[PDB]
Amino acid sequence: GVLYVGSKTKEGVVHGVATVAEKTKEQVTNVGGAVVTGVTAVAQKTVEGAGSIAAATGFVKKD
Amino acid sequence: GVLYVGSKTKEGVVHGVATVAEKTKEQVTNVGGAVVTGVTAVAQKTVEGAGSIAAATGFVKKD
Amino acid sequence: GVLYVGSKTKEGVVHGVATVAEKTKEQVTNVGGAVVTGVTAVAQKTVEGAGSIAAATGFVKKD
Amino acid sequence: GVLYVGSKTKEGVVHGVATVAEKTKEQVTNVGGAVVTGVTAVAQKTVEGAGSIAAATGFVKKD
Amino acid sequence: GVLYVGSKTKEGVVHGVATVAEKTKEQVTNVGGAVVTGVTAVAQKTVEGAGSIAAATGFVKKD
Amino acid sequence: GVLYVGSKTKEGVVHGVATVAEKTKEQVTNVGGAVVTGVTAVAQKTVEGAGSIAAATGFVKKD
């Protein structure tokens, strides 16, 4: 169906995903999949059917 | 069906996902799937059918 | 169906994915999949059918 | 002596002298002398010594 | 002496002298002398000594 | 003496002298003398000594 997204903004400031680490020993940073960001952000029908977004993180450390 | 999203804003400031760590030993940061962000954020029909978003984090540490 | 995205902005500032590490020992940075970003961001039908976005990170450290 | 005028404003709207006439027969409009106007208006020492500001209006109509 | 005029404004709108007439028979419009106007308006020492600002209007109509 | 005029503005709109007439029979419009106007308007020492600004309007109509 119709999906109207109107917008009349002014001086719009947007930050998306942020991350900060410090003085750690090990570091992992996995990001993605459907990360949309912006003054007019739209994300329609990210997954349909048998599709998958397996944004996993297999941290094992098999000590 | 119809989905109208009107907006007349002014001086809009938006922060999305934030994360802060400090003085840790191990660090993991998994983000994503359907992270939408913005002054006019829309997210319609993220998953339909047999689809999946398995944003897991298999932290094992098999000590 | 129709998907109208109108926008009349002015002085729009957008930051997408950010990441900061410091004084760590090991470092990993995996990003992607469907990272969209901008003053007018649109992301329609990222995955359809048997498709997949396996943005994983196989950190093992098989010590 | 010192005359400090500090100001940190935002979205300031100022109107100065206004005048409206309607359906009259005769019309006179004398303005001036020291008409200062603005978001940061200052008017120091307008008249000193034998000076004068004779903003008169000699409407006579010597009928 | 020192005369400091600081200002940190944003989106300042200023109107100075205004005048409106309608359906009149005779019309006169005298303006001036020291008409200062603006977001940072300053008017120092407009008249000094034997000076004069005779912004008059000799409407006679010697009928 | 020192006369400091600092200003850090943004999106400043200024109108100076305005005048509107309509459906009149006779029309006169005298303007001037020291009409200063602007986002940073300054007018120092407009008249000094025996000087004069005789912005008059000798409307007689010696009927």
Image (tube, coloured by chain):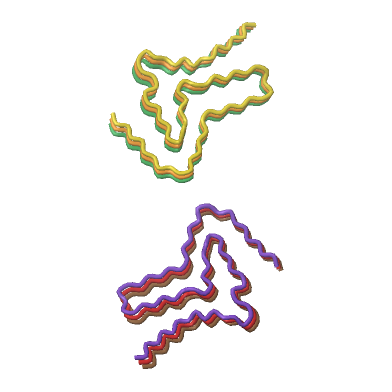
Chain colours: A orange, B green, C yellow, D brown, E red, F purple
Q: Is residue B4 above or below residue C51?
A: below
User: Does residue F37 appear left or right of residue F2 in this picture?
Assistant: left
Relative to D4, residue C2 above or below: above
x%, y% of residue C58? Answer: 55, 11
Residue B58, by quadrant, is top right
User: Which one is in front, C13 or B21?
Assistant: C13
Q: Is residue A10 above or below residue D19?
A: above
- x and y percent of residue D7 in the render? 60, 58
Where residue C59 appears, as percent x and y from the top left, is 58, 12
Q: How many marks?
A: 0
Q: Front-most of A44 and C4?
A: C4
Q: Give the left or right position of residue B49, taking residue F54 as reference.
A: left
Is A48 on the left or on the right of D52, as rendered?
Answer: left
Q: Quadrant of the C terminus of chain F?
A: bottom left
Position of residue D62 measured from the top left corner of the image (x, y, whole percent): 39, 92
Q: Is residue B26 above or below residue F61?
A: above
Q: Nearer the viewer, residue B54 or E38?
A: E38
User: Which quarter of the rendered picture does the N terminus of chain F lie within?
Assistant: bottom right
Taking the spot 68% from the left edge, 18% from the top edge, the residue there is C25
Horizontal arrangement in the rendering, residue A41 relative to residue C1 (left or right): right
